[PDB]
Length: 128
Ligand SMILES: [Hg+2]
Ligand SMILES: [Hg+2]
Image (cartoon, rainbow, N blue to C red):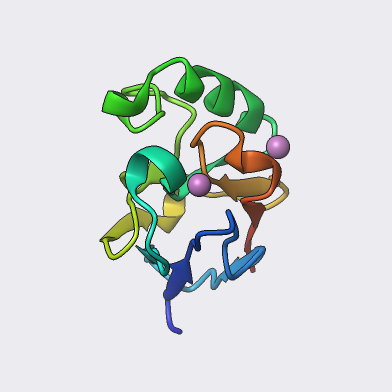
């Protein structure tokens, strides 16, 4: 939709998109995350985390080490452009971020930092 997208993470460790386009005219962009299924956060938690592609691995690694009580995301990580909280089934979280934090000629990735999820739960985010 305009300057916004709705995203689902399911019980099979899947997002329902692997590619997000952000319209350059947008002043900010919003992601609304939900979690179909019936499994809880500790088992099948999802978040939506944005970083440059170059920074993704560092964020994933430091997030795992941060623990479940930190939503598997390092607090105040300067590499995380925007993020939701970790959610289980039946829950919702959203994030709005300034589009000025993105540039052209930079590859962005979105992913989930729950342990082992990012191998499957990841995609591209592009400003155009
Ligand atoms: Hg996940
Ligand atoms: Hg990556």
